[PDB]
Image: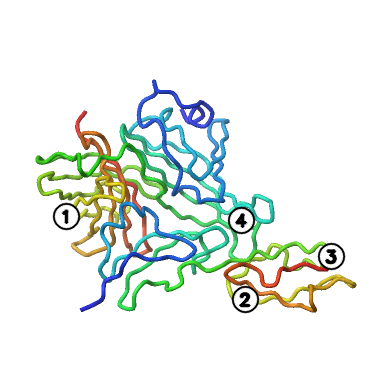
Amino acid sequence: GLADALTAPLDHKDKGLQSLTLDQSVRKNEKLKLAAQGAEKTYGNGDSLNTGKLKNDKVSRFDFIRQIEVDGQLITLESGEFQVYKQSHSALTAFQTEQIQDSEHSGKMVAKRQFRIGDIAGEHTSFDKLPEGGRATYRGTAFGSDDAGGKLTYTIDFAAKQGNGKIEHLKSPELNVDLAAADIKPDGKRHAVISGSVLYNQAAKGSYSLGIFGGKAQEVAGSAAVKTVNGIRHIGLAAKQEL
Amino acid sequence: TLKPCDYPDIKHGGLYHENMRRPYFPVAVGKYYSYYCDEHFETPSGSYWDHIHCTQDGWSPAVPCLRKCYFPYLENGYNQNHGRKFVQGKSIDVACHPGYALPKAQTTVTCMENGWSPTPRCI
């Protein structure tokens, strides 16, 4: 239900995650206009996105237009597909660009394809409220440009406050990376966060960032950056425990 | 031994996922992070976002966010450069209509960090 997400307001009866604050998806004085199934809505840095109407453990797809006010007029910067991955206590956004503004002329749109991770939000797990011991296994999706079929496996030893994972089944082989052993550290607001190295053929290709979401640390959500023969590639990460 | 990189103070921009990245600084040489540029500012590649790299000499690019000036429409001037984009430091001449001129006998404008200097206007 893509149209309801843009038109219908916030309702507590809808499946979680109900709301998502668009911060890293929309810059301060820029506008992001989303359109799907005849519906249309504009945002808004700090504006809420009704994720509640969207289906869980799936990629929700919308058409996007990114604009900026130049001389009191909204000029298009980039356009393409806006992706939203929903889970119970977490959710994340991604952008697949199809058209961008010409380097030399504003108002002239050129065909360029860039994939980037937007926001990673939800009900953050407190570092001070994490389980004192035990091992948790997280299973979910890893998704890049033109591929949402990747399968993510992540493991957290709560006694050691350390995590390790793996990405599999992505079409691009260089993206099926290992999420190296990394320490869970407290955030500025004291949220449980994990950041470590990304490896392909036991060589460092980038970094990964994850946030622990849910009261009982039910989920993990974040992203990874991988160096490939054709450039730096971004992977959206989201996994959950057994319900 | 190589000097690690402390948190990058990206002027006129910042790092994406700041909350998750900040507790792990200083970072080793070779580490790279996706960053953004604020309104009117661009990355050396011409986008609003790119990647900053921790090298032997420090953060690369050294100037991650450069100013981008969009040439305005001149009400009483020639509009050959109307809507053209210019990187920070580049200079362009302002051709005004007969009887009109840039205030205080000026003809050339330059893209600064603040924007166009002086303001491109005819009379």
In the foreground, A227 or A47: A47
Give the secondary structure at mark 1: strand
Circle 3 residue? B76
SS at mark 2? loop
- Does label 3 lie on the same chain as label 1? no
| Marks 2/4: CA–CA distance | 23 Å
Q: Mark 1 points at which residue?
A: A181
Tell which tag, 4 or 3, sits nearer the viewer.
3
Would you place residue A85 above or below residue A146 in this image? above
What type is the residue that disc 4 sits on? Met
The quadrant holding residue B81 is: bottom right
Which subunit holds the residue at mark 4? A
Query: A168 or A162: which is nearer to us?
Result: A162
**Amino acid found under the numbered disc labelled 1:** Ala
Identify the residue at image location x=69%, y=52%: A72
Q: Which amino acid does label 3 sit on?
A: Asn
**Disc 4 designates what residue?**
A109
CA distance separating discs 4 and 1: 43 Å
Give the x, y percent position of residue B40: 58, 61
Question: Which comes before the other along the chain, label 4 or label 1?
Answer: 4
